[PDB]
Image (cartoon, coloured by chain):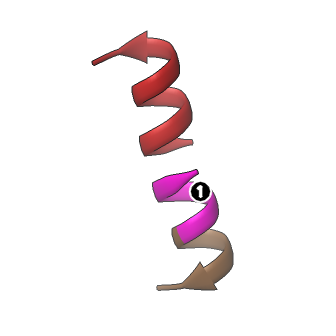
Chain colours: A brown, B red
Amino acid sequence: FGAXAXVXWXYXWXWX
Amino acid sequence: FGAXAXVXWXYXWXWX
């Protein structure tokens, strides 16, 4: 979750 | 992964 990877920001779901 | 939850910063493994 959040800023890095998973869901949120960076790598996976949500946004860059 | 990273800043939020999972492994890294915030909620789960690593650091606050």
Residue A4 drawn at (x, y percent): 47, 55
Measured from the top left, where is residue B10 in percent x and y?
A: 37, 29
Query: Is B9 above or below relative to B1?
Result: above
Residue A6 shown left or right of residue A8 in the figure = right
Task: Assign the C terminus of chain B to one quadrant of the image.
Answer: top left
User: Is residue B10 shown above or below A3?
Assistant: above
Q: Residue at the spot x=54%, y=69% of the render?
A: A8
Residue tagged by mark 1? A5
Residue shown at 59% from the left, 56% from the top: A5
Splitting the image into 4 quarters, where does residue B9 fall? Answer: top left
**Neighbour class for label 1 at 10 Å: few (<14), some, many (≥20)?**
many
Secondary structure mainly formed by the magenta segment: strand
Viewer-closest of B16 and A10: B16
Q: Quadrant of the N terminus of chain B?
A: top right
Seen from this angle, which residue lies furthest left? B16
In the image, residue B2 above or below residue A16: above
**Residue stretch in magenta:** A1-8
**Which residue is rendered at x = 53% and y = 37% of the image?**
B5
Residue B14 coordinates in the image, percent (x, y): 44, 12
Q: How many marks?
A: 1
SS for dot 1? strand
Q: Quadrant of residue B7?
A: top right
- Height in image: B9 above or below A3? above
Q: Nearer the viewer, residue A11 or A13?
A: A13
Who's the residue at 62% across and 68% down the image?
A11
Amino acid bearing label 1: Ala
Among the 4 quarters of the image, the one containing residue B6: top right
Chain to which mark 1 belongs: A
The answer to whether residue B7 is magenta is no
